[PDB]
Image 1 (spheres, rainbow over the protein chains, first blue to last red):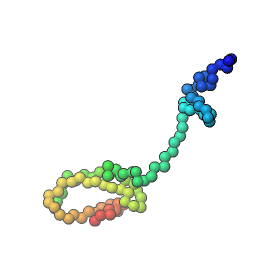
Image 2 (spheres, chains in turn orange, yellow):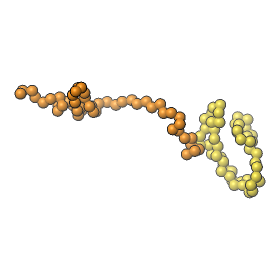
Image 3 (tube, chains in turn yellow, blue):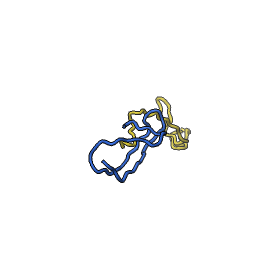
Image 4 (cartoon, rainbow over the protein chains, first blue to last red):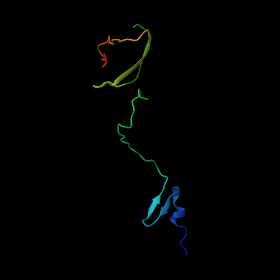
Length: 49
Length: 49
């Protein structure tokens, strides 16, 4: 009864939390590095373009 | 055949063991025929003769 607002409503940065299992979805915090090792079949030489 | 209005553009070049340089030469000729290509500079070698 005197439980107050859950973390679903009070957590900053718009985190959406689901359970079974417990997880925090779409917490807009910081940035992220992504590395792509692209194969060589996808590329076309400048002269062919 | 004789030629005129020759221009040379290198859209992509990489100094490597393989043919890493490609050059597109726009020209105007006079008639159809076989022409020899030769580099007057020793630092460049063309695969096609």
